[PDB]
Amino acid sequence: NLQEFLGGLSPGVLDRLYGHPATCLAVFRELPSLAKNWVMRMLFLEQPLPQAAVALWVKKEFSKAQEESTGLLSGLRIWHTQLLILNPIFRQNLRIALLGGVPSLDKYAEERWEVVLHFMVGSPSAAVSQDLAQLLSQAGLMKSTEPGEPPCITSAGFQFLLLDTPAQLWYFMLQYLQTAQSRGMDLVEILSFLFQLSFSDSLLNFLQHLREFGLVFQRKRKSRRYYPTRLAINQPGFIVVETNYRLYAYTESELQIALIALFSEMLYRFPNMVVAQVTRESVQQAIASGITAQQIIHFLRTRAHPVMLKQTPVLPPTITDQIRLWELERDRLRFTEGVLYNQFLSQVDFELLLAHARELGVLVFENSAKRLMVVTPAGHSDVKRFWKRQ
Amino acid sequence: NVLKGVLIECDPAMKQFLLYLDESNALGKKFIIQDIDDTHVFVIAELVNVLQERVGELMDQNAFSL
Amino acid sequence: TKVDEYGAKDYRLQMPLKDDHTSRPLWVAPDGHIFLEAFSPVYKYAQDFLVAIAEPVCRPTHVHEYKLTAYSLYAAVSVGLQTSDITEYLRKLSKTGVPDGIMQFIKLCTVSYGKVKLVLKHNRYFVESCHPDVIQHLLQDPVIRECRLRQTVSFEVKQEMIEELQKRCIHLEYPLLAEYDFRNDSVNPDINIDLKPTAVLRPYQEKSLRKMFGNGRARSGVIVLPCGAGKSLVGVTAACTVRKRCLVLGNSAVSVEQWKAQFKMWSTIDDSQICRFTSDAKDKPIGCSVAISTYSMLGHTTKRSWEAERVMEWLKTQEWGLMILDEVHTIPAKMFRRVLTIVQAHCKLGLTATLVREDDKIVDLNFLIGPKLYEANWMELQNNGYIAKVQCAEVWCPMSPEFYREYVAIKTKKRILLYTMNPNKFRACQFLIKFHERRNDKIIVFADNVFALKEYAIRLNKPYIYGPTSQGERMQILQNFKHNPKINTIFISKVGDTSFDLPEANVLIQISSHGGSRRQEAQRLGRVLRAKKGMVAEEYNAFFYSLVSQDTQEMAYSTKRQRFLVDQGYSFKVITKLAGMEEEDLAFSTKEEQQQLLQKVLAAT
Amino acid sequence: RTKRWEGGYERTWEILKE
């Protein structure tokens, strides 16, 4: 989440990131419940106040909210104890932020994201962009290993594909920022633009990438002014599930049919409908590719036709249980690398080694009755060194 | 002593299937280095992929092809 | 014919899409498959039309699946639906048009009907036809000449070769008409049989009877209805409507007894006018007309007793207005099917509840008797309350380690006796029976292996029944099960699924299965479908458990066996573990007991 | 005295027209 992203930052980058135009407001909106009130209170104070007052300024009931808010805002470093006055820079910027100082766009964003997903999947016809391809490859969801041949899809790719559009896009942009730092693009400058959206060379390249993703569209031959789409700021279902593992999806866009075929066997394709079967072969194929039953169940639930919404639960228990059992059977045999021991002359030495392995985290499994244990190869060197030291 | 390989944990039915495999030399070798517990055994790392393939064939046997 | 990048066939360039597709709830695939919506406001009308012109293959709650064939179209024409009368409404209902392939198929099937009619008169089967060209171009192959005994053109045909000629015509594209004009028939006087007002006909029974009597002439066909739905009542009503000599064919002594009881209960016909052509007991079969007999006796191939020979000769000589055949799924058998040619009947109605089998001989029924007239909607009956709602479940029992060891080690087929008898399933069935016994639910345990059945029954000191069990003891056990409160469970063998009149049971556990037999599965499931006096559909008072052993051939057999039930719509819920099993004390709680059971299994040989 | 079945098929859909 954005809270995680901002928490994972240093004070030096934080205060700089607290730009005047928007950041002080975007980070404010993050404040879940109460920290908003305290920020407004001590927005006008130039004198720090004791911590005991803040501690006692919440009733005995619901105090956990007080501690969690205080910890979150301490991590954000909005104030300093100075002994709890807010940062002067943040105070000034917030005062300046508080009385101081479309139908075609959404369709465009939808179409651009749909073609991006088409390229992500093995679609013969898709938009071509070397920068987009390499960005997705280095995002960790795609690996090529051969420039001549089109890149394939890794295990994480299918999991990313089956996610809902909001979380999918949010994770994609998170990876975009993480790779932006690696490629050398300044993180603060690009990050501030995202906050400003909800209200230089690097800026131009970043805006080009955002337009390729479909969040923005200049509409004027790449002019300075931009009109963000709905997705920039941050629908009814169509699948009907039977009790015989049969899916009838009212899908016209090839993306939905491809997503369903990823874990189901297609039987018929009507102009406004498609029939597929959820069989062991397809489900285990998806599981081997990397998906887990949770993603499939969530995908079918979110793309649930209104007809089956009346019944509770929406997805039939038999279908859900069958999918879960199919995924479990694959991982019945759990493989874990390790090193076995044999010929323990005395149990005292074995117990001491067990205690050492428990302390170091090396141990994976132990058997006192048989006087043996298993250690991962990483801890094999440590235990071997201990044995040599005697 | 110290023995290289991998440890696999599964239900007792699969453990007994692995014991049958090693006893009958289905794969040609006694890959079961030792039996850690009723649900845990040790097998050589190199053979694990084909052992998993055999288990998949067993699942094919015990599951109908809808 | 066109295949997309995936498995599904491509029809983007095949047929168009109607603009008012949302209004139209019907789909039409080129192969003949039709997908109807159960949520559309016109669902009832669409269901009626599609049932009239097609036979269901899958009817889940949301989207029903039908497929039409030559036999279904012939049945539609028999009930009087013309090619236009069906195709115009099919196009109107269809939200994506009608492919030219289906159009031409419907036209050809409808036009190729009624040209050739088969009528039996004075013990002679004449192939009548108003059009003479049909016969002129039908006498090309020599089989017709060798078959024939050595406008409105008709010729006599040999009795024995009727089945061969009929199956030949089916693929010759000239189906024969078996309609019986009982209204206009003076050769055989009508029998004094009437339907008393006491009998009550349910709406689905009336619909099936209407489809059979689409016109004044009765149609010969097969009506599939659940055993608890009153198929016996439907057959009795059909005979009463026919008002002519009726020959009912059961499959066993219990079947014939039940048929006689149903006749007496629902028909005003006197007792003396009904006979039981049964070797065990007879009531002067030649004396009266309405007869109940058995396939085994009629098709008996070995030496015939003197009295049975006289009765058989009388039956062969006489002509029957109606030939009712219960449990038609066994008809395509050699001896049983020989009875069709042995006996003469205008219309041979067929009744059953499980019209499914593995060998592809069910298709032969379409010509042996006729097209499948009606097939009751099990889900709709459940909603209407005519049939008790069933919570179908499959209890997965993990196989014990040692038992799995021998099972996998041996490549022989002792596994049938092995996995059917494992400690985990034994404990599961024991705990389930205890839970239902304290819940006052009647239990009917099932097991194909008599050895396993006997072992379980002795260990649980319960009254197991099986083949060579004495009839008196069988009746005593059934009476005790029905009446004595102290006992609420009976362990029946395969004999249970064949034919019986057992009291309604709240649960039905199946520890073992004969194999991938949809027939047996449906037959055993039908036992608990008996609707209670005041139950409700949503209460799920009836339960069916099909215990299976994990990681064994039993799983494959169960999955292959539940196909018919899932097609009807029942959802089999999987139960990996049962709550309270650990706390409840059960047998085989120690390794030693499993060891002795394994030793006994091994010594079984 | 004939039965309702002999009359003919109900034709439940014939009521609906478009």
Image (cartoon, rainbow, N blue to C red):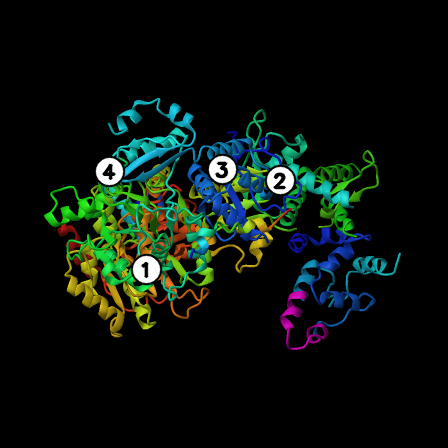
Whether residue C78 appears in this view of the structure is yes
Q: Is residue C205 left or right of residue C49?
A: left
The disc numbered 2 marks a residue on which chain? A
Q: Is residue C34 left or right of residue B16?
A: right
Instruction: Give the crowd class for mark 4: few <14, some 14-19, many >=20 residues within 10 Å.
Output: few
Q: Which residue is mark 2?
A: A252
Residue at 63% over, 49% down: A167
Q: Nearer the viewer, residue C11 or C75?
A: C75
CB-based contact (under 8 Å), mark 1 and mark 4: no
Q: Which residue is mark 1?
A: C527
Task: Tell me the quarter of the picture where residue B24 sits.
Answer: top left
Q: Secondary structure at mark 1?
A: helix
Q: Which residues are magenta?
A: A53-69
Q: A297 above or below C479?
A: above
In primary-sequence order, the first of circles 1 and 3 is 3
**Disc 1 versus disc 4: distance between alpha carbons?**
48 Å
Q: Is residue C400 left or right of residue A299?
A: left
**Disc 4 versus disc 3: distance between alpha carbons?**
52 Å
